[PDB]
Length: 360
Ligand SMILES: Cc1cc(CN(C)C)ccc1-c1cnc(NCc2c(F)ccc3c2CCO3)n2cc(C#N)nc12
Image 1 (cartoon, rainbow, N blue to C red):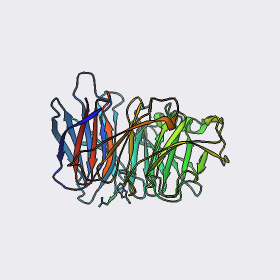
Image 2: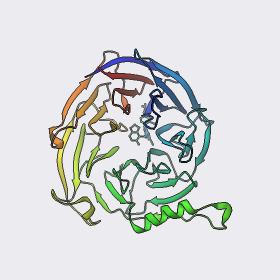
Image 3: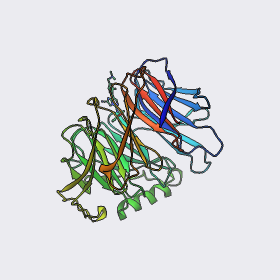
Image 4: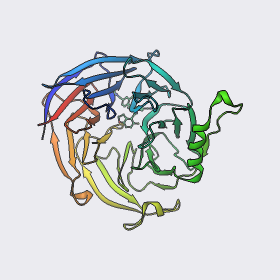
């Protein structure tokens, strides 16, 4: 029951590739979201009567930078929100959302960064996925690279998406090699690495911080999709992943009754629990998103149509779909974002337009 209440367009006329509401905003503060596109990050505030108030932007010094992704966290000691952005240059920037100052940056990836994700229980643990075939886990409190997830048995082509499970114990990643790979970060090795990353103070020691080199996933499959897998999210112990085949697939590793934490790296079976089809979304680089409670799933297509699946049903394949269109919204929707209370849905487009849908 969403209604389109407003729209606007950014003056660069370049694609907006990412949008994220700040779910770490304090009580009583207005709902804020960020857009990324061109070499720009922009913050907007949502107000009554559909108003989208423009606040302030961060413009990268490199006019050739192209931001692909962003994610919110908060500064661990001060509680003030932080915004991480990254894109074609392969550089993570940490932005102060109040002043839009770049506080610090992380270099290391060999090519573009395609997605950023923060650990669900630890606001300092930032996951990056890169065109260089690797994932990196960063501790943005001590400014340390904790681990590199790669190798010959890592991804063999550009990594496009990844996601932490609910408790932050494991990561699922996906990309251009058609594969989805599980990486457990609750192993004794990775837990110890995270602890050491917090005890590292370069002014109190002579050593560099040693990163972990993780070369072997804990599960891998190429049997879900037959093309680029450009978005992946956990839904409990299940996985939602999409390709460019007009399909979000709900699946799990192993057979039907196999526990996710009993899965071994040699597991060769998967179980398909359903498929959410849609129309006209066969270009690469389109994300679906879920609300905070994971009751709803949203995806835009390449002609401006929005699909919303109600996941509050007993089984994945029973999901109920509703569609949202506007006669003036005809450009490809790259990503969407629900506000934390799920009352607002924002969609961003290849023509730099922004569309606001309010639950009425
Ligand atoms: C730079 C770019 C140009 C175009 C063509 N113009 C005309 C529209 C299409 C696509 C990308 C493009 C977009 N988004 C990423 N990444 C981020 C990413 C993703 F990884 C997976 C899904 C997803 C996104 C954004 C929205 O969902 N890109 C990466 C490269 C390269 N190389 N090109 C692009």
